[PDB]
């Protein structure tokens, strides 16, 4: 068993309803238990800005699944919640489930790259992560508290 940390995002189709449904669905992942859920946060879109604000959260998920098996399940949940791929890079979506961390694992497979490649630059990932895991240390030894103390991230407001 290991603890995975998953980022949640939604900016379409009633984000509060999409995230609450995703949390129920994450509890149905086999060989896995939710440990902790962050507050929900209403965040301005990074990347393309011509889209609605996001509801962002994070979840701690204790699992004995393999990393890619966990990825199968989060992809499934997205697809089952009406996630449709458009050609636009970084367009709006009903649900996004990003594996931020999988224990202390460092993975760069075809389908899966962990830690999430850009999470240490995203307040919408790190603030909810700190709320559920203040003592977190990344695979490379960097402390989550230290990143947030040192680096400028806009203030996050709750939903
Ligand atoms: N840590 C991870 N969590 C989830 N998917 C990941 C992943 N690392 C790689 N992937 C791969 O990422 C592919 C594209 O996912 P998308 O959701 O469209 C990117 P996004 O989440 O919009 O951008 P971002 O990764 O910059 O946040 C997935 O099909 C999956 O194979
Ligand atoms: N607030 C908010 N904005 C979001 N933009 C995306 S697309 C990826 C992306 C692209 C460039 C960048 F610099 C940061 C994130 N996903 C988001 C999310 O979950 N929340
Ligand atoms: Ca994402
Ligand atoms: Ca994603
Ligand atoms: Cl899309
Ligand atoms: Cl979508
Ligand atoms: Na479960
Ligand atoms: Na656009």
Image: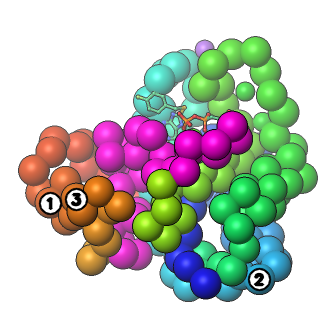
Q: Residue at x 41, y 39 (%)?
A: 118
Residue 141 part of the magenta segment: no
Q: How is the model colour-coded?
A: rainbow
Label 2 crowd (10 A; few <14 / some 14-19 / many >=20): few
What is the C-alpha distance between the residues marked 2 and 1?
A: 33 Å
As drawn, 108 above or below 106: above
The residue nearer to you, when weighing 132 against 75, is 75
Q: Is mark 1 within 8 Å of ligand 2?
A: no
Query: Mark 2 = which residue?
Result: 31
Q: Position of residue 147 (x, y in %)?
A: 19, 54
112 on left or right of 25: left
The residue nearer to you, when weighing 119 against 157, is 119
143 on left or right of 92: left
**Dot label at residue 98:** none
Magenta-colored span: 107-133
Label 1 crowd (10 A; few <14 / some 14-19 / many >=20): few
Q: Is mark 2 within 8 Å of ligand 7?
A: yes
Label 3 crowd (10 A; few <14 / some 14-19 / many >=20): few
The residue nearer to you, when weighing 29 against 39, is 29
User: Can residue 14 be seen here?
Assistant: no
Q: Nearer the viewer, mark 1 or mark 3?
A: 3
The image quadrant that residue 88 belongs to is: top right
Whichever of labels 2 and 3 marks the residue nearer the N terminus, that label is 2
Query: Mark 1 = which residue?
Result: 146
Quarter placement of the N terminus: bottom right
As drawn, 27 above or below 156: below
């Amino acid at each position: 068993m290991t603890v995975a940390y998953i980022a949640i995002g939604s900016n379409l189709a009633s984000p509060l309803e999409q995230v609450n449904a995703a949390l129920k669905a994450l509890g149905d992942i086999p060989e896995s238990h939710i440990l902790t859920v962050s507050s929900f946060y209403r965040t301005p879109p990074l990347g393309p800005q011509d889209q609605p604000d996001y509801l962002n959260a994070a979840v701690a998920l204790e699992t004995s699944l393999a990393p890619e098996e966990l990825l199968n399940h989060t992809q499934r949940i997205e697809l089952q919640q009406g996630r449709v791929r458009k050609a636009e890079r970084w367009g709006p979506r009903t649900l996004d489930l990003d594996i931020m961390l999988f224990g202390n694992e460092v993975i760069n497979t075809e389908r899966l790259t962990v830690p999430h490649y850009d999470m240490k630059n995203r307040g919408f990932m790190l603030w909810p992560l700190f709320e559920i895991a203040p003592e977190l240390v990344f695979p490379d030894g960097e402390m989550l508290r230290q990143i947030l103390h040192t680096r400028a991230f806009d203030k996050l407001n709750k939903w």
